[PDB]
Each structure stands twice: as structure tokens, then as C-alpha cells.
Image (spheres, one colour):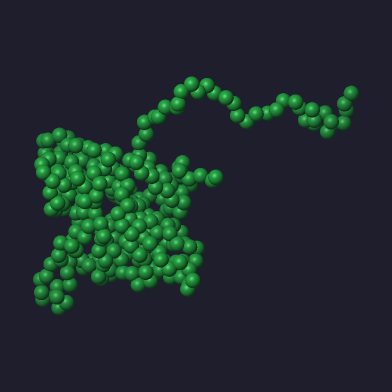
Length: 245
Length: 50
């Protein structure tokens, strides 16, 4: 009655019989931009069902040695379905997100994944190792797309900050002996009412194993982690030709 | 006449076949109602037990 759940939006429905409730980032549901917060004057377009639906974008394999991965929003969807087209044809974009991370195993497997959302997740480099070289991360690392990217130094989140304090952000855990999914609802987070879906990534989704995956020889060794997400209250403005970046 | 209790309280002889279902008029296919996104716990229409 808190373990079972159904998430229906658009022409897609998700089910889970081993949930752990739902998290609503910073305690507030997504919403459309009010006429007093807005600034751009053109009438926005709100596609609704064609873009506010669940998209399953990627599957990673959880291994005994995995370090963790991250994805950037809205980067992950800029080239998928109708949402992508609208993000490409419009200068302005804004929306919320419902993130559903899936990972099931057996009552004999163990391990725990920390699933968290970190706004304005700026990536840092190791500065040439000695820290005397001012290097910068490449586009494929700041905006990895749907395939995401693997963390090199999870302890410091590849940005000189302690992952041990990541729980100060909207998060959930996937502890195999307890639940097989994590659901986080995120409102639009920015210092502006609208912004570019291409140049700016509002937040990053981190999925990091804190307690290593383990099991005995003979049990299914392939344990996938699938990422499904849905935009909420998508709004677009500033129409012109399509642009990919 | 009847005097012992089990006899007085028995259902032996009930000729009324109890019915769990009943017919409703259905001259047309059912309509479709408007629906919106639902993101709840506890509620799960999609899961069944065939």
C-alpha cells in the first residue's frame, strides 16, 4: 500500500510491486510559469501528452566493480521523440521531471544504489593530476546525452565535493533487499523562468552504488539498471528553425 | 410441527437460487471518459491476478 505503485502519464504506464514511496523534490510539484514570473511575451506552446510521457532511454549493467554513472537533464531527451523536436525548434524551454530508476534482483542478491538529483551539476577535471594544469571537461562529458557517463572519482563526485553529503539533495536508495526502484519528482529549478534546453542542464541524475553488488556463483550475474523519465508541464517559446546545439 | 433448533434454523429447502450478478441495459458500446496522469502508490489497476 506504499510498496505497490502505478505511474500513468501520457500513453505510458509504469508499475512496481516493491517501491519505497515517492520523493517530491524540495517539497513542490512541477507547475507552469505564472504571468508574473514570465518575461518573454510570445504565447508559449504546451504540447501536453505528446511530450509529457515516460521515455526509457538507457540501461546500464551493475557490476561488482561499478563506480557509478550520471545523466544531465534535459540533455538526455534533446534528441528523443516529440519532446526533442520542441527543444530543438524553440529557444526557450521549461519543465519538471518524474524520474523512475529500475533495478530488480533476487532475495539472495545484495547491494545499495544511491539515486540523487543535483541541480547545476558542474563537472570538474583532475587538473592534470598535479593540479598545475587548468584543464576543462569536454562536451561529451558535460552533456553525455542518453548514454550518460561513468564517474571517475565517485568519492568527490568528479567535482571536488563529498558524495557522503549528496543526500542533502532529493534522493532515494535502491537497497535490493527492500525495493527495486526509485521515483523522484523534480520541479523546474533555475534562476530564470525559461532557458535553453541545449546550453543549460538544470540538474544531473546520479546513480551510485554505495554498498557493492554481491551474490554467490550460480545466481543471475547480469543485473541491469534502467532509466525511465517523463517531462512534466513542458512549455516552449521563441520559435524558429531546429537547432541541435 | 418443528421444535429442535437445528431444524428451525436450517436452510434445507431454499428454492431461491441466489445470484451474484444481474443484467443491465447496454444498447451501445460504453463511452470513454476523460483521464489525466496519475502518480499514486497503493492504486494499481494494471496489476491483476489471473
